Image 1 (tube, one colour):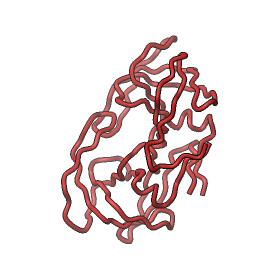
Image 2: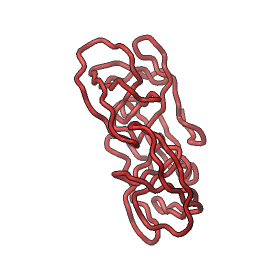
Image 3: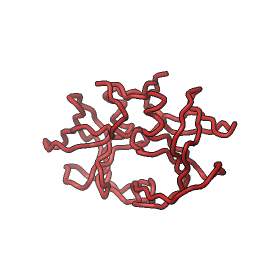
Length: 99
Length: 99
C-alpha cells in the first residue's frame, strides 16, 4: 500500500498467531514490541530515545507478519505504548519513504 | 526522492538560514530540533519517548526547508540528541511510506 502521514501509520501485524497493532517507524533502528511471551533465550540490550536510555530484552529470529508480509529478525521487548517496527524489519518487507 | 531504510533517513534542513541535519521520523507526531534560538513566543510542551519525557519550547508558524520543499509548522526546541522531522511537516512535503 501507500501509507500517508495525516495520522499515525498504525498497522495490524501478526505474531504467534496473534493480531496486534504496530507503528511503522523510520526513526527506529530496531523493532520494539510490548511486554509479551516470546520463544527462547534473550540477551540484554540498551536503547535511547527522547527520555534517554533504557535496557530492554532481545530475541532473535522472531517471525512477524506485517500486512501479510513475512519478516524474521531481532525484536526487542520493553515498555512502550505501542509495538514499533524499525528499519530492521521495514527493510525486509521492502518499505521506502517517497516524496 | 525515494529513500531506502538500509540507513537512517537523515536529510539536510534549512532553518533560520542555518542548515542542520535531521532524521525523517514517522514515529514522531511533531518536529523537535536540538536547542537553538528562533523568533516568536514559545510555550512549554512536554514530549515523551523511550526513556521518558523532556520539556521543550514550542514555536509555531515556523518555516523549514526539507530537500527543497518549504513546509510550515510548529517545531519544538530542546534536549533532543538528534534533530527530528515528524509527521507535522512530513505531510507538508507529501511523504508516504510505501511497500
